[PDB]
Each structure stands twice: as structure tokens, then as C-alpha cells.
Image: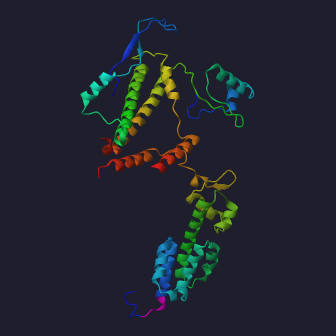
Amino acid sequence: TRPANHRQLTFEEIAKSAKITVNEVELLVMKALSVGLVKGSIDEVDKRVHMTWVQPRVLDLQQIKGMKDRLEFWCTDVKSMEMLVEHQAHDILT
Amino acid sequence: LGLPTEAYISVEEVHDDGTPTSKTFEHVTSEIGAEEAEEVGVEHLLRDIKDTTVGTLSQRITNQVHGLKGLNSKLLDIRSYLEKVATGKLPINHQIIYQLQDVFNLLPDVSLQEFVKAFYLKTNDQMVVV
Amino acid sequence: FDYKEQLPESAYMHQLLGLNLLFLLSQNRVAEFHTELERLPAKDIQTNVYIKHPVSLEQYLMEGSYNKVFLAKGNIPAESYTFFIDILLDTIRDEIAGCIEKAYEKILFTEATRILFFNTPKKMTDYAKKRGWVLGPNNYYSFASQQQKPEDTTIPSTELAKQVIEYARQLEMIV
């Protein structure tokens, strides 16, 4: 459910969500990483667990609609930059 | 754009995750290689539009533009497929679709402070040489 | 100026001249003030009082001597001065407000009272609605939203890409 930009997770949200102590989230994310569903890293001074993903999941109609909207935004950005590049580099293009 | 050949192999399995079975044509990647005699034959056959293999700035820039065009085309095709799936005109695969989700997760997330500093450092390192 | 060599110079012009200079102080047109000062002869810059007063006021304003301006307000020889002196008071208060914006980041009302030469807190509520300075949790006006730290997180990229494109063009032009 993270917005894919602030992928870092704080300790308190994990403790309040899984209703577990703040000393157990560390071992829990360690176990999840060890199994092969997470490829992040663990910090302690700030205790923010860095997050990267290699374990996908099942989608849904609303999720598919939202994610195809995101893909449409991505393709629009790609097209805009391609147009800018061809316009600016018209003479050099050949 | 390219790749006028698509290689397909018949596979037969229970589809693992409990779905009705069918023939299906699993895709296998393809590429265009050449034998030395065929290589000299084709190079002499063109002899009028073959670009310089050294590249130079104009052809590198056109290669970059071609890459942007190809990426836009691929994203457009993927978006059309996703629209077909969402509208119900195509059934949700429920699998491989999450490999496209893996595409979505693999975004580098630029504007990160460390990445920005490293990017500026290398840009200046190239700019001084330029 | 055209007929200086033929017509005399009654004191009145100096008065008006000084007013003119002080006029620019009322309008913050300091550059025009210095040009007009250059127009006048060097002797009259420091000899004539009508020219001396705006020169001294601008010099005090140029070294941050706002207190010197406030105390020298009473050294004017005419009410024609007095009007532009009042306008200069508003202009100098605005200048002090701008300096406060650019220099500091948090400002206290009580010491700002001495800073801006306001004898009534409602005369500062005037700026609190005119300038609309945001009041903090502990009556501390915050200007950290003025300086800020932008452009250090997002790579321009597009502009740099256009610059690199121009480099390639200038390298590949036949000319």
C-alpha cells in the first residue's frame, strides 16, 4: 500500500498494524527478507526499513484501472520527451 | 520498428494454478544473426543506405530517438492490453500481469539525494572533458 | 539648466531641488537620486541645506542608519519637506520589512516594535494584514518560506538535454 516513492517503513506503523512490539518488527522483516519475499534493508538509528520488491501479487479491477492510469502517465511523459528531443535535434538528426 | 520474426513453441501443462488446459503457444525470443557469406552478401546488397558502423553524433542521436520511439510504442501496446483487460474484453491473466507490476516496481526513483549528487558529479566529470 | 548662464538662482530652486531628491527617497528611486545628485554642482551638495538634508538622509539610509533618519526627521526647514518625510517614513518601514524578510527567519513582535519604529501594536497589525506575515505558534513571524531550498532535489535534465542537443548541433553543422 506504500505510494512507491516513500517506500521506507517506520517502526510505529508496523507495531500498530501487526499489533506486535517494536522489538519484534525487526525480526519479522528479517524473516520475510530471509524467506525470499523482500529484498530491502534494515536501519536502526532511524529504524526505518528500506524497501525493495521482488515478490509480486494478484491484482484487481480497480487496481488495474489505477495502474493503467499510471502507465498512461508514463507513456505520455515518454512521448513528450521524445517530441522535445526530435524537435530540438531536427537538423543534427539526419 | 524491428524484429520481423516471432518464434513460438507449443507447451502442454496443467497451468499449475488450477485453470482449464489448452494448447497455447509459449513465446521464445528470436534474433537475426548472419553467416559470413550471408553477411557479405547482404552488405553488398544494401551498399546505398548502410550507415557508418562508427556511429558518430548524428547516428547516436537518431539511435536515442529510435529508442524513445520504441519505448513509447511498447508502453502504448501495454496500455492498450491493460485497457482491454480492465474493460473485460480480455480476461485477467492473474499471472505475468504481476511481472508487468514488477516493471512498475523497478522504476529507479530519480530525485533521490544520493543519486542526484552522484549524477551531478558524473555530469560535471563529463562536462569538463567536453 | 538651459538658462543657468543667463538667469540667477533664487534659493527656491534649491528647496525644490532638495524636494526633488527627497521626492525620489519617497519613491525609493535611489538610482535617480544619485544621478540627479551628480547633475548638481559639487559645491552645493554639502553647502546648501536644502540639498544637504536629502543627501544626509539617503546616506543614513545607505548605511542602515534608520535610527539616524528617524532622529533627523526634525531637521527639516519646511512642511513641503514634511510630507515627503512622512512618505519616506513609510518607504523606510517597507525597506526594513524587506530586510527582515531576507535576513532573518523568525521575528518576535516585541523586539520588532523597536526595530520598525512603531509606537502602536495596531500600526503593526496593519503590516500583519497588509504584508500578511504568518504568525507562528509562539507569536513568532516565520520567513523560512521565503528563502527555502529549491532546485537542489530535481535534476533539470530537460534543460540540460537541450543544452547537449545544442552542443551536438554546433558540432555537426556543416558551417
Is C11 contained in the magenta span? yes
Q: Quadrant of the N terminus of chain B?
A: top left
Image position of A19 with respect to B59: above or below: above
| Residue B14, x across and y down, in percent | 49, 5
Image position of C157 with respect to C132: above or below: above
Image position of A7 with respect to C41: above or below: above
Q: On the rendered structure, is C58 left or right of C156? A: right
Give the magenta-colored segment's residue range: C8-12
How is the model colour-coded? rainbow
| Residue B25, x across and y down, in percent | 40, 11
> Residue at coordinates 49% horizontally, 71% vertically from top-left?
C27
Q: Is residue A72 visible?
A: yes
| Residue C163, x across and y down, in percent | 41, 49
The quadrant in which residue C122 appears is: bottom right
The quadrant in which residue A47 appears is: top right
| Residue A81, x across and y down, in percent | 40, 39
Q: Main secondary structure of the magenta part?
A: loop
Q: Nearer the viewer, residue C157 or C84?
A: C157
Q: Is residue A62 visible?
A: no
Is B119 contained in the magenta span? no
Q: Disc count in the image? A: 0
> Residue at coordinates 49% horizontally, 76% vertically from top-left?
C33
Q: Nearer the viewer, residue B115 or C26?
A: B115
Q: Nearer the viewer, residue C80 or C108?
A: C108
